Each structure stands twice: as C-alpha cells, then as structure tokens.
Length: 89
Length: 92
Ligand SMILES: [Zn+2]
Ligand SMILES: [Zn+2]
Image (tube, rainbow over all chains, first blue to last red; front, side, top):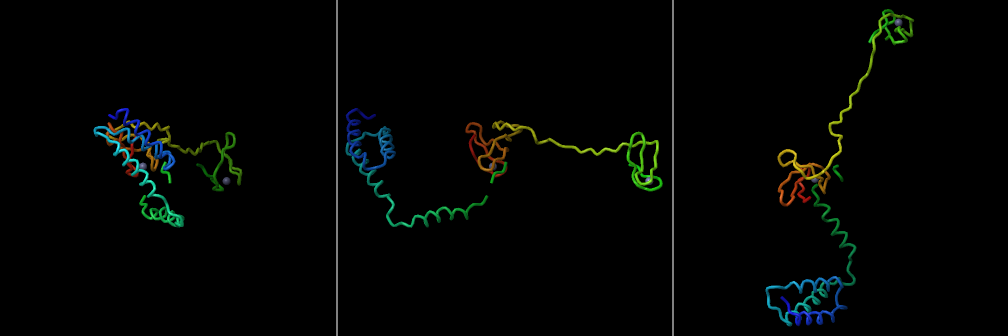
C-alpha cells in the first residue's frame, strides 16, 4: 500500500523524464511501480528504479553503420533450415 | 445385351423392335440396357467444430496449425487439445 505522499513523489519524479524514453515504456513503468505491494517502498528506491530504467533503455539502442539487412536476412533464413514439418500449407 | 444372329453386331432398340443397322434384322424380344453409377456421400456433411467429445477423448476441433478437425481432449478444465494429424497442442 503506497500512501498519497509517496504516490505524489512518484508522479512528480516521473514527469521530468517524459522526453527521455518512448511513451509505451513510460506507461509500463508507471503501471509496474504502482503494483509493488508487501514491501516498504522508499524515495531512493523510486530514484534507482527510474534511473536504471532510463539507463537500460539507452544501453539497448542500435548503432549507426550496422549492416542490418544482412543480419535480418540471416535471422530470417537460418531458422528456415530448422523447420521439420484442410491441411493448409 | 444382344447380337444379330447373322451379322453378329449388337442390336439396338427402336420402337418395339431391335434392329441391326448393318443387315436389317428384327426380332420380337426387347432387352433394356442401363448403366448405373453410384455416388457416395459418407463424408460430405457440414462440420460443426465444437470441442465436444464423441467417443472417449476424440473431439471435433479445428487445428490452428494444419487445419484438421480431429483432436484429443487432453484436459477439460484447461480446454487443452491435441491435433491427431500433426500433434500440435493448443487451447480452444
Ligand atoms: Zn446383323
Ligand atoms: Zn494439426
């Protein structure tokens, strides 16, 4: 059970990162933090969760110059050799 | 089936007579020849695929993978099925 003070702190701390990640990720983070029960939650915990989420998103970005066409072709065609079978095709 | 006693060709029914076209023979006996073909509709009814068992665990259910309508009800509470054609396990 999160009291109104901590909920207000969460809402204030979540509104300054709206431009730092995609909207769906922000919604998922907000929905996930509100479901924490059985643990006494702290402001430092919220800070760490938000910072780790932003850092984790930033660390996953693709790099310029990547030969993504060859990688996509190899990722699609490689499992094609592992396929071992109205009676649709 | 009848044949002409002289020419040997087959006789066809014309009116009350059977006439040989090659020799003109005729007779008072008439024999009817028909060709009958049978069509079977054992498996042509309309299928209704509700996951209800018929005998044992054999149910009628459409497989999402191959599309066969034969399934085995593996578990009733989860509605868990298994295709009998490709062994695919699914939920309906
Ligand atoms: Zn004849
Ligand atoms: Zn199947």
